[PDB]
Length: 129
Ligand SMILES: [Cl-]
Ligand SMILES: [Cl-]
Ligand SMILES: [Cl-]
Ligand SMILES: [Cl-]
Ligand SMILES: [Cl-]
Ligand SMILES: [Cl-]
Ligand SMILES: [Cl-]
Ligand SMILES: [Cl-]
Ligand SMILES: [Cl-]
Ligand SMILES: [Cl-]
Ligand SMILES: [Cl-]
Ligand SMILES: [Cl-]
Ligand SMILES: [Cl-]
Ligand SMILES: [Cl-]
Ligand SMILES: [Cl-]
Ligand SMILES: [Cl-]
Ligand SMILES: [Cl-]
Ligand code: NA
Image 1: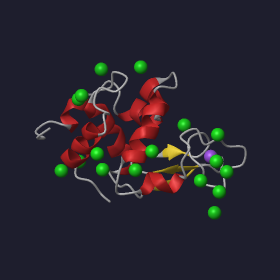
Image 2: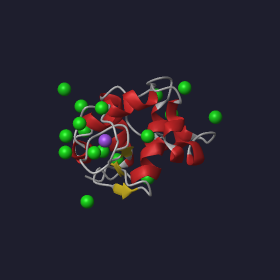
Image 3: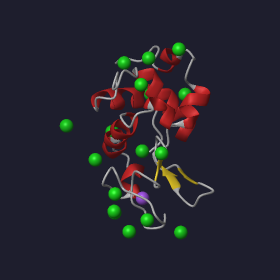
């Protein structure tokens, strides 16, 4: 599924991500924009052999099982394929665990490099929310 910007904002809010761990909704929309361009089916292979999955590019080294990441964990207790669904529930629930792991949204390097310190509210501006 490729979400629209305001569509994704609304779905994230429906699932309780708005202001989760203190991160306003625009932070989450910005992260999704640069991780996946709002495409739930996004995947990307890392040099280490892990893979990132879904709208928030959640990595198989720690967070989900794909059967092909030696030595990895599955802390969200899900197949990585669940993170590619048109329904963002699994991605949101796993992101809540990730952002609670101590480093906040710095867990997403693209958030740190492209969203942190910017006008992230622009990502939700104009949306009926
Ligand atoms: Cl939209
Ligand atoms: Cl956009
Ligand atoms: Cl429901
Ligand atoms: Cl918010
Ligand atoms: Cl915001
Ligand atoms: Cl996703
Ligand atoms: Cl990670
Ligand atoms: Cl497992
Ligand atoms: Cl497996
Ligand atoms: Cl594995
Ligand atoms: Cl493979
Ligand atoms: Cl595990
Ligand atoms: Cl599994
Ligand atoms: Cl959804
Ligand atoms: Cl879930
Ligand atoms: Cl924080
Ligand atoms: Cl700031
Ligand atoms: Na894994």
